[PDB]
Image (cartoon, rainbow over all chains, first blue to last red):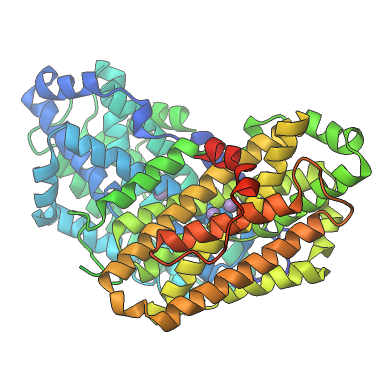
Length: 296
Length: 296
Ligand SMILES: [Mn+2]
Ligand SMILES: [Mn+2]
Ligand SMILES: [Mn+2]
Ligand SMILES: [Mn+2]
């Protein structure tokens, strides 16, 4: 098998196991119109202290920075990985991103955050985030399979599996602790599950590429993956600092969120056979174990 | 205002009305696992005469010739029509085609038609159908916007709005008259509604292209569209002859199916401002009015 080459017959599948990702998204499928956000609008308006409102506002803006955008990467994977089973997953994933866009676009509207969203791009922390996101996808349109592989790798391991996860954690933790933001936490939980599925497929694709082209993955390029991992963590850790610019939440300190992120980065590296990059404080990490127990 | 030109900023939308197509497919969304085909399997095995079974088998094979294939045209429209609103529709449509593929692939399996499906491509009537289908999409990957426009036009007006519709009509008519093939007619009705939506969006895209580039739609190019309309009808009319090779169904004669097809071809031409091509026998057309009353 060669993942990069087109095949003559539709059947049999060369990577039949990838078909499970279509079933996974059909099971996770959701539209924001299934949730009721009336209490969330009221909570955001009058139920929060100024510290809590600033944290929630910034978290919603940070999710939207990624979700409220044109996201065609998954829908285009078939051009460079021309397999029917990959094209099926890619199309299923591309549609799920349209559902995410509509959900967060609706949430910015009803929370009265459209003007703040338009001005978000001017923030240095956001520009720094955009830099690592654009660098990660610099080869998304490359004619070289090895360069394109770098884009899949960084996109799946770090963007899909980690970029939004401090934000998903903040919303879920807020609902778990305060029983507020019911509709938003439902939408966030549904988005988390789909991003987890997106990254898992990308991890599987990378392991197929690595199995078929082991010589592309030397100690040298493994060091290049590790420095991109560090850049992603530093940028996301700074986004966390900005989210809590008006004060930390006592039940979810930044130190707890940072350990949660480092662990996700480690798991992404380990998923493709690399060694872990971050030393983990187990006691601080334990505080967020409930998140993965919910997402699965 | 140019449909072919990239707009990086998400809002304001240039064609906000195209968003209705994403909501239309979310409303029509279905998976074959929502239907029960147990009675259909039994009907196909023991409930049909030799004439009826041959007609149903050939109809299912003809639907599958189009549906059981990699269908990435809709998911790629954004490359040449780089608008966020178009990209959202394209991704939603590309996913619906994966659902259609899984549905008809499941139906070929449970009806024991996998081997007959593998050999279908060798039939002269099928080769003749493939010829007009491939000719219609010959410019699907062109760098010239005018040539690409020809592919969208033929694909939407004739392939999406008509190619499968004699088959959808045959299945629904069989269920209406005989109260058999319950699950299959449900899946066919659900597919018909989504193909109707697919072609409607394509018609809207063509009318935007025609509004922005009226000089592209000259008498010479309109004559080519009419010549392609005739080629599509002749090939689909021959597919109908093949479906009924073992005998016609008294309740749905070929003359009735052919008038149904000619009328659909006329409506596609009229939808983009071209004149009707076929003379219609109104009495024979009236016999299939119930079909559009169900789909629309
Ligand atoms: Mn998303
Ligand atoms: Mn994703
Ligand atoms: Mn279809
Ligand atoms: Mn279609």
